[PDB]
Amino acid sequence: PQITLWQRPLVTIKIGGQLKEALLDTGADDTVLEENSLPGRWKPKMIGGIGGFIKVRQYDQILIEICGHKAIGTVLVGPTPVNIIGRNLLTQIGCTLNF
Amino acid sequence: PQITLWQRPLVTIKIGGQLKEALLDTGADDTVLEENSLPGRWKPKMIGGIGGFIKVRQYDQILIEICGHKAIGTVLVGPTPVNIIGRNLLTQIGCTLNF
Ligand SMILES: COC(=O)[C@@H](NC(=O)[C@@H](NC(=O)CC[C@H](O)[C@H](Cc1ccccc1)NC(=O)[C@H](C)NC(=O)[C@H](C)N)C(C)C)C(C)C
Figure (cartoon, each protein chain N blue to C red):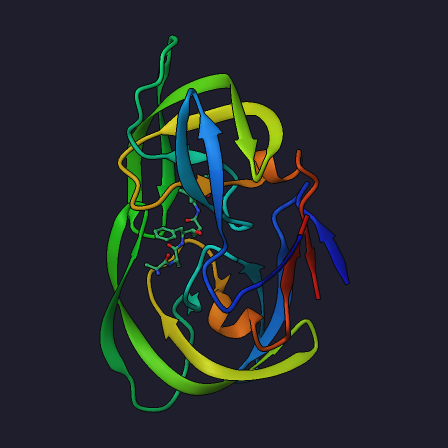
């Protein structure tokens, strides 16, 4: 599909059985989603945003269906305002920027 | 042009006589650039990112050339890690997301 930026780019995702909406973010090197009930072993890690650094929990090799497109990656869960689809995933569903 | 997300999406901009590189960010409602020597009257304002809120200085009706494309908008200057091209500008050079 084709997406114009008049409105924030939101999408429907399916992660470990729960249906959420995420934001397609080209300025995000990483995939970071809110606190969700995720099972597996994780690791402490830090990431930065305009306002600073939140400690996240780093889960790898998670299955996520983006706009009905299946991908597999590292996802980090933390105290984020909005869920974000970063470049580590957008490359996978082969997302391009155009102008 | 066509842009794949293997590498952060960077671009060359020209703002009030100085040549900088900015990041094309679809998850950014707003254009926020580092401290630059900008002239005109401004206003205090707050914005939020994953890590919080920085007070910015809000300048409106600024001329900015994006990848050799001229646009006019509100730009906010602040203590940001990287310059960002938000949606208020990407709509103007008619940028779309594609998948
Ligand atoms: C209003 O609600 C909001 O969400 C407010 N905030 C926003 O819209 C903000 N957007 C946002 O907060 C959306 C996320 C931005 O794209 C940042 C940009 C960034 C890239 C590289 C280094 C540092 C920062 N990405 C990130 O923070 C991503 C997750 N991670 C990184 O950049 C890491 C450190 N590599 C802007 C301040 C950029 C506001 C504009 C309304």
